[PDB]
Each structure stands twice: as C-alpha cells, then as structure tokens.
Amino acid sequence: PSIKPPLIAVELENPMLGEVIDLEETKAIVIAAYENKALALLFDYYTGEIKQINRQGNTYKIAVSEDYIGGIFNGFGEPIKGPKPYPEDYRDINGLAINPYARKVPNEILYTGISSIDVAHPLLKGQKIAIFSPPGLPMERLALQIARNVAKDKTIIFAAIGVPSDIYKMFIDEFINTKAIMNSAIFISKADSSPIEKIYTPRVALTLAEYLAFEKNRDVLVLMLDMTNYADALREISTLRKEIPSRRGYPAYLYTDLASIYERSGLTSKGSITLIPMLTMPGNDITHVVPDLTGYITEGQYVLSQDLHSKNIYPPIDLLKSLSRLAKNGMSKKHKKYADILIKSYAKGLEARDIATIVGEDSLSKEDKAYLKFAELVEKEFIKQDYYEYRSIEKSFEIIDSILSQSGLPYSP
Amino acid sequence: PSIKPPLIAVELENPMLGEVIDLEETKAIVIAAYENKALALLFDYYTGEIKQINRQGNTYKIAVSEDYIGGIFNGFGEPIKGPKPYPEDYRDINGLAINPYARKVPNEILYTGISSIDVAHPLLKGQKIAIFSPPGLPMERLALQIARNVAKDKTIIFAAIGVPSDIYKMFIDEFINTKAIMNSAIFISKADSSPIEKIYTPRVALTLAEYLAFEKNRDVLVLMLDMTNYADALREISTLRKEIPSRRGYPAYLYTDLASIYERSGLTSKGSITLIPMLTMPGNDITHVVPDLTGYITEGQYVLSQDLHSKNIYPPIDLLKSLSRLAKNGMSKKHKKYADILIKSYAKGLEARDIATIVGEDSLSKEDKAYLKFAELVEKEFIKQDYYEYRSIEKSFEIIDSILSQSGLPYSP
Amino acid sequence: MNRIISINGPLVIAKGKFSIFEVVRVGEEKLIGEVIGIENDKAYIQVYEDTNGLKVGEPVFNTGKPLTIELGPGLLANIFDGLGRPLKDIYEKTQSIYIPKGIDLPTLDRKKVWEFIPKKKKGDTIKGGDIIGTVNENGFEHRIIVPPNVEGKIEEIYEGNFTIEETIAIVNGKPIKLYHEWPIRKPRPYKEKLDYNYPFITGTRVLDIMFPIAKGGSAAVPGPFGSGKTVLNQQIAKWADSDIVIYIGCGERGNEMTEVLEEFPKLKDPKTGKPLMYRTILIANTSNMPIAAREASIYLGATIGEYFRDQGYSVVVNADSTSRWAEALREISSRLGEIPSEEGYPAYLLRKLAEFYERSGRVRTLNDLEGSLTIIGAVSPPGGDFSEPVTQNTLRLVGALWALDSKLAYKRHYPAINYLISYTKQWEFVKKYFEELYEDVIEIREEFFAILKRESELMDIVSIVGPDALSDNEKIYLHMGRIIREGFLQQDAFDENDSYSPLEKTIELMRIIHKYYVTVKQLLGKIPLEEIEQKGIHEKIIKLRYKSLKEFREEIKAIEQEILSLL
Ligand SMILES: Nc1ncnc2c1ncn2[C@@H]1O[C@H](COP(=O)(O)OP(=O)(O)NP(=O)(O)O)[C@@H](O)[C@H]1O
Ligand SMILES: [Mg+2]
C-alpha cells in the first residue's frame, strides 16, 4: 500500500473509476485505474493503516428526498447536526446532461428589488448568472440580499466551497433571521476538508436541486461560493494524477468540468433551477482562467467594482461590465427602453468623465457635463442602495426619470 | 508494432536515420533510431497493418532533370497530374552547404517595377529576401506581381507549404494566365498532408533549383509559402520524438533548420537562385519566433503594413521596417541618393505626423508640414501602385522628384 | 476476448484485435467509441459517452465500419447530437429531460413515409452522385443522390410512397435506398473545385459590404465572452442566402440550441416565405455533453454539408464554437501521453483544423451540378487574446476575419465587429457582383473605410487635446463616423425591422449617407459644422434601420428633400 493524506495507493482486482471503497472509519473515491493499481482520495483525515478494504458496488451516490430542506450538511451530503434523511432512491451526484429539446428558455424575470440589477441586467427564472468580485468586496452580502427578494416561495440551496467559517456562518445566521432556513438546504465543505469533498459540494447540491425541481415540481434557487476555491480543489486532484497541467497548474478540462456544474440548471414545464455561482477574481483580473471560463459558460455576470466600493457605494455593481444574456426575454417594451437609456447614457457619462481628465470639468461641451452629471447621480442614487431597501421596478424607473430630469436630459413624464 | 497516424513505431536491425521504408501502398521516413527501435512518419493516410516492411538502402532522394518545368507536383516531388519525370541521377533533398569561397556576392538588381521596392530596397539576383505579412494582407498578390516582372527569362519554382486551396490555385491560375507556367515548376503540400511532406516541400524545390542553376547554367526564382506553416510542421515532427521543446513548442534548432533552407540560394559564375520566403506574422508580431529567426537569416525583408492596408494602399509595404541588405551592391550613385532622400524624408515626415497628434496640424513648423505633405504623397502616389502597373526606375525617380516639388522640398530638375 | 485495461476520462485502452478507425462498443452498456491508436496488442479508444463507472474487466465489442452518418430525408427541421442521434426521439423514447448513457436510436426516421419521384427511367445508366429522383421534404426538393460507389445500369426503379429502408431502385443487382452512410472523417468527393463567383449574402450589413466572403468561402469569428459570437452566427443562420443551413452547437450552452428551436419555426425565409426550420439542421453537443463528441459534431455537420452540396445546393455551416473542439483534442492528447505543444494543445492542432475548413469551397459535383459549402467558424480565445494558437491557426486557413471587439461590445455596439482589425481575402472575387448591380457602392465602401480610419486616428488627438478643439475639416469624420457606426454598422438582432437587412436596405443606407456626405463637404467654410448638426438629419439617418420597409423608403425621400444645401 501507500499513504500520504489525503491520497492513498492500493491494489484492486478490477478497479472501477469513481468507485467508493470503505476503510475502518472513513471512505474513499477511486480517481485513477490502471491495471491492478488504483489511486484513491480519503474523505477526511485518516491515521489508521490501509489494510482491510470494502468495495461498494458503485460510484458515490446520495439518497434524495425533501428531508434535506431545513438541514445543514457537509460536502458529501452527510448531516452535520442531525440526523440522516430518508435513505431512499440513490442518485449519482454527477447527474445527466439535460436534453436541450426538453428545455424551455427562461423568459420570466425574478425581480431582486435591486435597481442596478432589475433594470439593465435582470435575472430570469431558470437562468444561470454569476457574480464576479475582486477580493474584499461585499459579494456575499449581494447574494444574500438577492436571495431574500427572489426566493420567498422557492427553496434555497447553498453550496459552501472551502469558504472560511466567517463566510458560511454569515449565510446561515442570515437564513435564520429571515426565517428562510426552514425552506433551505445547506452544503458546506470546510477550507481544510479533502479536495474530494470540495468538488462534491456543488454536485450533491445540484443533484438535490434537480430532484426538487424536475421530479417534484418546484422552483429552486442555488447559490455557490467560492468557485475559485472549487478550481483550486479540482487542480489539487488533477495534480495527484499523472495529468499534464495547463496554465497555472489548472487541469486542461477546467471548462468542461465547470460546464458540468453550471449547465445543471434551467427551466422546464415542471420546474426550474436558478443558479448563481460566485467567485473571487484573483488579483482582480477578469481575464484569469476561473472568471474567464465562467463567463464563457454562465448566462451573464454581475461584476463588482473596486472603484465604486472605494466611493462607498453598495452594491458596487459595474453597470457596463455586467451582463444578463437572457434579459431581453423577460423585458417589456418599456423595460427595454429604460435599460437602453440607462446603459448608453451612463456609458457616455463615463466617456465625458475621461475627457474631464483632459479639458477640465466645467470647460467642456454643455451636453458632456449633462452626461457627467447623469453618471454621478446614477452611482449615488440609482446604483447605491441600502442592503435592506427593496425597490419595485417602477420605483427604479422613477429614479431614472428623476436623474434624467436633474441632468437636463430627456425624461418621460 | 505501433501505429497512430501519421506516426508508426517498429523494430529494425540496424536503423538508418532518414531511411526510407516501404509498406503496401505508402512509404515512410525514419526520424528516430535507438538500438533496434525506430520511429517513422507515414507519407500519407494509411489504414493497413504495419507488417511487411521493405527498406530502401538510402534516405529520401529525387531524380533531377528539366522535366519538372511545366509540371505540378506534391511535397515529395511526385507528379500530381502526370506523369513521372526522367528518373535519372537521384539527389539527396537536403543537399549540401555552399562553399562561401565558391560564392559570388549579388550585385545585379532585379527590377520589379514596384516603386516601394526598386528605389530604397531593391532585390538583387541571387539574393534571399523575405516577405513579412500580418494576417489578411495581400502578401500573395505582391509575390505574384514580383514574379511577373523579374522572371521573364527565368524559371520560377513555387513551393506551397500547407496553404489552403484558395492560395496555391491563385498562383497556378496566375502562372497560367501570364503564360509563365510552362517555364515553371510547382510543389504543393496540402494543409492536411503529413508533416514530413510539408517540410520536404521546400527541400525538393531547392534541390531542383540548385540543379537548374548550378549544374545547368540558369537563373532561378524560388518562392515559398507559408514559412509559418513550415515551422508548425517541423514542430509537429519535433514533438513526435523525445525532443525537449523551446518556446511555444518549437524545436530549439529552428534557426539552423530554417538556415538549412534559406542558405540554399545565391549567385555564382554559372547561375543564381533568388529566393523569396513568405510568412504570416502570428498576431502581427514581428518579434514572434518565425519572423524573428527568418529576419536573422534572410538578407532583408519586405514588411506589409496593417495601417497602409487600412488606407486602401497596395502594395502595403512599410518603407522603414523593410530592408534589403545587399541593395547597396547594385545601386548607382544616383540610385543611392534617391533611396537616401526617400527614406530620411519619409521618416522625418512620420516624426512630424507624430507631433501632429500633439500640436495640431497647421500649427507647427513650416518645414514639418512639408515633410508631413511628403509622407502623405509618398503613400498615395509612390507606394500606392496598381497590381498591373509596371514602373521603370526612372519613372519612380520622377514620382519622387514630383512629390519633393509638391511638398516644397529640394528636387532635382 | 476484448478487455478494457484502463479508463482515463474519455480515453479507454483495451486489449484485442482492432482497426485504426473502427467504432467499438465499450463496456457492458456498449458505449459508442472510436479507436484512434494501436500500440501492439492495445487499442486507444475515445469514448463519445460518459466513461465514469466503467470496470476494468469489461468487454469491448467490435464493429465493421467506421463512424458514419445517414444521409437522406429526415434531417431537415430536426435536432441531433454529436453522433447524429435524434434528440426529439430520445426525449420521447425515455420520457426524461436528461440524456441517457448509451442510448441507441436510428438517425433518420424509420416510420416516416416519403413520396419518391424518380428522375431516371428503367434501362438508364447511372454514375456516382447521380440524382435518381426527388423527395419533397416539407417544401424542399431533397435530391436522392446515389453513393459515389454506385455505378451501372438501372434494372428497376419505383415511384410513390416509401420509408427510409425500402428499396426504390435496383442497379446492377444491388438495391438503392433513399439514403446512404458516409464516413464523417472522409471528405465527400467532387469533380472540380470552382472559382469564387458569388458573394455570400448574410442578413448583416457589415458582413455583406465591409468584410464579405464568396459563396463557398470561409470565415472566422473570434472574440471574448459576451462579445456576440453566438448571436452573430444565429443571425447568419437566420437570414443567409442559402438552400441549407447547418448550425453546430459545439460545446456551448444548451439553452441556445433550445433558443433556435423556439424562434426558427416562428420565422419566415425572406427569399421563399417558407418557415426557416425547413431548411435548418441542428447539431447539438453542448458543453456538459461528452467532450469527445464535440469533435464528432464538427465532422458530422461537415459531411452533411457536403451531402447537400453534392445535390447541387448551396450550404452554410456555423460552428459555435471551434475552440471547444480544440479543448477536446487537447484532452485526448493529454490522456494519450503525448507531448504538449503551444499552450497545451497537440502539435497537430493546425492540421486538425485544416481537416474542417478545407472541406469548404464552391465545387463541380459528381453529377455536373453546381454546389457550395460555406463554413463559418467561431473561436473563443482565452481572455480575449487573439494571439492564442486556435485563433492564429485559423487565420491561416480561412478567407476572412470577422473579429469581435471587447470595447465595442462594452459600448453595446452590436455587432461588435472591429472594422480596423477585420479583413476579407475574397473581395476581389465578389466585387464583380456589386460593380454590375450597384456601381456606386465600391466608392462608398472605400469611403466608409476611409472615414472610419480617419476617425480612428483622430481619437488619439482628442483624448489629449479635446474633441471640440478640432477643426471642422476634422470634426466631419467624427460626425460621419458616428453616422456610419450607429446607422449602418450597428444592427439590432432583436428588433423586428432591423434584424434582417436585405441588399436593397443596405445599399440605400449607403447611398443616403454618401449623399449626405458630399453635401456637408461642399458646405465647409460657408456654414460651420455646429450649425449643420443642429438641423437634425444626421439623427434621422441613424434611426432609419429601425423603420420598416415602407416607413424606411419614404423617410429616405424626406431626408433627400430635407437636404437642400442652399440656405
Ligand atoms: N446584433 C445584436 N443586437 C442586439 N444585441 C446583440 C447583438 N449581438 C449580440 N448582442 C448581445 O450580446 C450579448 C452576448 O451575445 P453572445 O453571442 O452570447 O456573446 P458571445 O459570448 O461572444 N457568444 P457565445 O459565448 O457563443 O454565447 C447578448 O446578450 C446579446 O444581447
Ligand atoms: Mg455559447
């Protein structure tokens, strides 16, 4: 045998890829299968000898039911507090790819009550949209605020991936306060956990999400964080094999693996899964492999601005870098017009802000100071919004019409 | 045995490096020789088993004669249409290095009729000069135009390396139209061909070129494209071995290998080989390994400008980035003066164009708007020239004297 | 006696007797795979299904032929996966929304009853690729072309109603079906590659005037995420002047394939009035579907494109996106223990890409008819850096670069085509079409390029000088450029009147902007540009593309009249 935590090497007769094997206390997942040799990842910290090994007949599967709702579990789906859900009907945590023929394209807006989102980049039911945040910005507060307003009739699933105690407890205590923890399931992998637990965290959460939404007829909201911690965990497992690394050590199949998670969402005739993956952009570089690949997969993204945050603005959402691909599907003619006037005028306002660095402010075109005024008010009145303030879509429109009026731009009254 | 196209592995008694071995239909080249083991590259797509193997006593050689003139062949020199040249006197396609003692330094200008070339950077007989082009610029049209005017009494050899059908057919149909295909030989390796065929394409072409020019007493013009496709082909073969890669996977001996091709040209007492290698600069980066190494080998280069092309200027030759090292050898005192006044004034015109971004045009030195006018007219009257327009060297001089006059600069009359 | 000896992702190594490109059934579930390498008694197999849960000792079942595709009636208006398996049938046969592991369904409908009308009589001699008859496929004349293999005299030929397996003719002792199977890794034969002759007319102005390709040409569409690759490709798939449209969903989002399924049946072909779906074929191997089938989908769609081309039809293939194919190749190469080349990709990446784009071209078919296959390839460069291998390799294979700009997408300037970096290498082959039918647009095109180029140069001076501190001989380019950009280059894919732009509308926009241009130029010094801009017009031209065919043509007259110069 061979053992260096959390990895072990052992001989097996006819090794199965992904096979679960049993030791004394802990389990393990076979991640490599040569001829008689096999590499396996321990579920946790194991001190004992790798002597007796019991081989389960299948890969890792979880029993699905509505018992997970209201409970807190680890990355393996196992209950932390207590006390084991109904062990009926086990499902492979990897699941299956959804037939695009059986899909329905999201067309219904889930209003968040957040102006910087609902107007220009609204979230739709069954949509997968991500949050891109530089280190240190209130990414967690934004997601929590969203979950309050869009999941009052929905089940929330939170997959905590390698996040510190400070982070996941913030979610838990907030689901408790808003009484939304009884209608939610939480899966948590600690920062010190085995890499096999971390990568299983989003899979077990989505396997339950698919069950609740497509076998039972429910609308599900799934949140996960941090996807950058997920990639680190996946790279750790990728390294333990002979696998030839891509850039920065990341596995060359990072896109496909991420896609195997982000694509496990959508809208059908029976139910829906709205997924919001969250990630920290390393060095605030959106071209980094994790935010880049994620943007190539998710149906848009909400980008947090390091500049807006320095201006004491919450939520620090960048209106121009952010995007909602399916937004057009759920927007009315009046809604489309407001998003258009908001985006193009704010963008023009930023252009006038750039030339203000050249020719001083107050020494420029008398429409360029109008767009300049517009951009400022948008940041300080439209984008800026309290963590406990909910705005109707009409209210957000009124703010725009107000700002347009103050800036000397054409407004609708 | 072992087989994954276009590579095979097999046992041989006493393996010879570069040895040609025979299968059922196709042949192969041994590219690696350990003890009893050998790695070989298939000539093309082969489905059969690697059973019976007939070993030719030597490396790849071609029979040389003047029969190639007027015919179209593949990268191996084999006739595509028909129908086998006189199989007499076989030559190793690698050839031999020319004794620099036996060389004569090029001193005779081959006038192209193209102002942007003949004046400042003229091509000489026996000279090796390359064309550097960003993706999408009329590099092929430039070479074709050159071949019309400089090879009316010469044999043209065209080595097509991995270029699409659109490209090599453009050459063929153009040699047909100008009746110059009867006095030319064409060697073509398709983009899907074996990498061994692609790297053999320039070698078989030059082996014939050396025969026609140095055994028969002829002046030969060799054109090849694309050298960037050649490097890719060479890297593919370099990878198939245990070879430790340099940057971007390219073999560490890329310079020497390229030199083994570019140096197979020159002038003697009997004949000459004028070689024009063509390459696409990846990402329009002249510091990329292929254009960089090529510039370290060729005796100058004609650099196509992405800016001039956007100005609807053909040929988009950059007068300042381009160079002809041996140009001085064939230039008269009057010719040297015109190149000098052209280069330094155009360069000064560009300097005045840069400061025009600072202080506006019309608000500068009244000699700086002169050089500014000069640079513009040079681009729009001197450099810009029709694909079917031939200019004598005197005509090109007159344009310069005309431009100098219009710009308020000293001219010769 | 075959035995799996290893399972490494999509790669399975097995013991036994195999062939170099033979399809195999991997494991007890008989998962479709393909041998790609043989090292002694071993065979290297890429599995087009999920390899998770595979045991070592499991068997590997041999088959006769290679990877093929059924070429006949039953493809149009349907969606298939990477292996050409019907996704509508999969859904119904399984009653699930998920895609099963190792489902085995026939490609063409086996029960659908077609009406066959022969174009040849008894006793006639037949060649390969000969039209033996036609089948009406929901308004489309599907020409039953016999395989290139088939030659001889017609001993019997039938007429009327038949299914896809029923014999419709007998030639030299052998039965002729309404379909045949062709290896997708094998380019279908043709007589002669023809010269470029006709411009490939999409519905999008920038791709029809600024950087057009010829019918049978090829183009690359690279850009970062959110730039507009999918929408641009879908817009081409919607309005392109083409007999057959093939959209390949290569390793991308599922919803976008569904998006086509919802909108295309609702839309009408401008050239025929018929619903767009009846000319459309969908190949869908989404991002989280088997990665090895991404490659298969590329070759599959290409073979189908050649098939309809061989009927003497014009076919267009949109591949969204080719980078996902490259990722698949990169993955196989890794597991195979191959040495990586540039950026991890195998050293044979360029040649592999060539096996796709080289299939394009306007050709002389075996039956001496004229057909063309136009291939549009989307590239997804990491970080939006175009210097990456895939993009760069592609640019030395295709006829034009339709580059999408991150800066323009940021401005919501759609399509985000970088008019400075983008190019076409096929303008000289298509200008003849325009020189004849619209002689004045050659000048206007050069004019639009020149204006955009001059506006570009002026932007450096502006940022460190001031936009209003310029002369009116300079400010005109900023003025005209904005009109060209917001009025001509931009095109709202999700607007009813703007989504499709016929050449009539496109040329009229060019003519009216040019007519406005020469008016302003001969008004300099006399009337300042500031005063001119106050009289609207420039804003009215911009909004022209949003108006209907009727509202547009009259507003043009209004603008022409509103241009009176003498004031
Ligand atoms: N012609 C257009 N008109 C209006 N909006 C457009 C147009 N083209 C693109 N867009 C918008 O651009 C956004 C991104 O489009 P999309 O094609 O998905 O980007 P992409 O990342 O480059 N391609 P892909 O990754 O394959 O989906 C969408 O939300 C569209 O609304
Ligand atoms: Mg996509």
Image (tube, coloured by chain):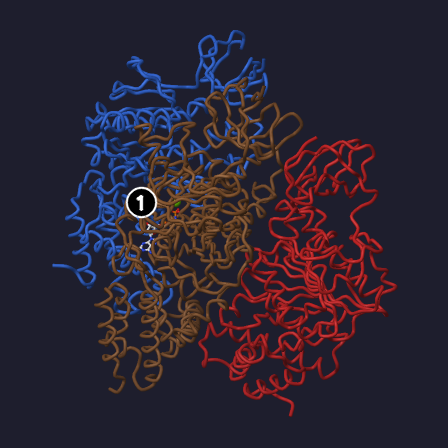
Chain colours: A blue, B red, C brown
Residue C287 in view, yes or no? no
- Left or right of C155? Residue A411 is left
Residue A117, horizontal then vertical, whole percent: 25, 45
Chain that bears disc 1: C
Q: Residue at x 78, y 37 (%)?
A: B33
- Left or right of B361? Residue B70 is right
Residue A25 in view, yes or no? yes
Q: Residue at x 35, y 72 (%)?
A: C510
Residue A155, horizontal then vertical, whole percent: 24, 28
> Where A183 sits versus B354, above or below?
above
- Could you tell me which quadrant the C terminus of chain A lies in? bottom left
Residue A284, horizontal then vertical, whole percent: 42, 44
Q: Residues within 10 Å of mark 1 (few under 14, many from 20)?
A: some
Residue A160, horizontal then vertical, whole percent: 35, 28
Q: How many marks?
A: 1
Tell me the SS state at disc 1: helix
Q: Quadrant of residue B149?
A: bottom right
Q: As rendered, which of B44 and B255 lies closer to the eye? A: B44
Query: Which residue, as the protein is rendered here, is positioned at the far bottom?
Result: B413
- Left or right of B65? Residue C268 is left
- Left or right of A338? Residue C457 is right
**Residue at which label 1 appears:** C259
Q: Quadrant of residue A191?
A: top left
> Where B348 sits versus C356, above or below?
below
Query: Which residue, as the protein is rendered here, is positioned at the far left?
Result: A413
- Could you tell me which quadrant the N terminus of chain A lies in? top right
Q: As rendered, which of C178 and B280 lies closer to the eye? A: C178
Kindly identify the amino acid type of the residue bearing the numbered disc 1. Answer: Glu
Does label 1 point to a residue whose CB lies under 8 Å from ligand 1? no
